[PDB]
Amino acid sequence: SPHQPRVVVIKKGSNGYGFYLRAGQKGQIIKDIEPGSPAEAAGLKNNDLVVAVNGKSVEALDHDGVVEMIRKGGDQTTLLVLDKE
Ligand SMILES: [Ca+2]
Ligand SMILES: [Ca+2]
Ligand SMILES: [Cl-]
Ligand SMILES: [Cl-]
Ligand SMILES: [Cl-]
Ligand SMILES: [Cl-]
Ligand SMILES: [Cl-]
Ligand SMILES: [Zn+2]
Ligand SMILES: [Zn+2]
Ligand SMILES: [Zn+2]
Ligand SMILES: [Zn+2]
């Protein structure tokens, strides 16, 4: 029985969120989490596929579109993520 999708809230720190996004070339996967960052502390990991931002599906979007969805939410973001194998 596979692990379920989950919601992770991250607040931007002085040095940003501390996660990055890269296509695996479908949806964006969380990558390059900075040690000691809000991303790490909130429970993101580097096989998380981002499927929604702030309740909005990002499944049809490219890198620029996912980035924009996140940036326009100000200084926090609410991600729905699920495991990529
Ligand atoms: Ca914008
Ligand atoms: Ca703009
Ligand atoms: Cl940032
Ligand atoms: Cl990024
Ligand atoms: Cl941002
Ligand atoms: Cl913006
Ligand atoms: Cl905008
Ligand atoms: Zn989906
Ligand atoms: Zn980028
Ligand atoms: Zn771009
Ligand atoms: Zn870019």
Image (spheres, grey):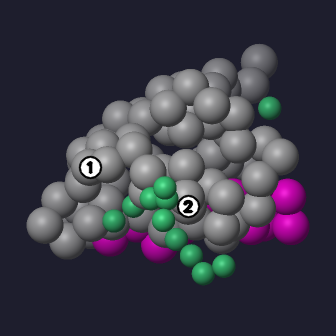
Neighbour tally class for label 2: few under 14, some 14-19, many 20 plus, Cα within 10 Å: some
Give residue 67's mark: 2
Q: Nearer the viewer, residue 3 or 62?
A: 62
Give, as a single range, the part of the protein colored magenta: 23-34
**Gap between marks 2 and 1 measured at Cα:** 13 Å
**Would you place residue 21 above or below residue 82 in this image?**
below
Q: Residue at x 56, y 25 (%)?
A: 55
Query: What percent of the width, then of the height, locates residue 80?
Result: 57, 33
| Residue 31 image position (x, y, % from top left) | 54, 67
Q: Is residue 29 magenta?
A: yes
Query: Closer to the N terminus: mark 2 or mark 1?
Result: 2
Q: Which residue is mark 1?
A: 75
User: What residue appears at the point 73 percent right and 48 percent down from the top-left corner?
Assistant: 84
**Residue 68 in view (yes/no):** yes
Relative to 20, residue 38 above or below: above
Q: Residue at x 67, y 58 (%)?
A: 65
Residue at image coords 70%, 34%: 57
Magenta span has 46?
A: no
Residue type at the position of mark 2: Val
Q: Amino acid at mark 1?
A: Asp
Image height check: is 57 above or below 70?
Answer: above
Give the quadrant of residue 37: bottom left
Tell me, yes or no, if residue 40 can be seen here: no
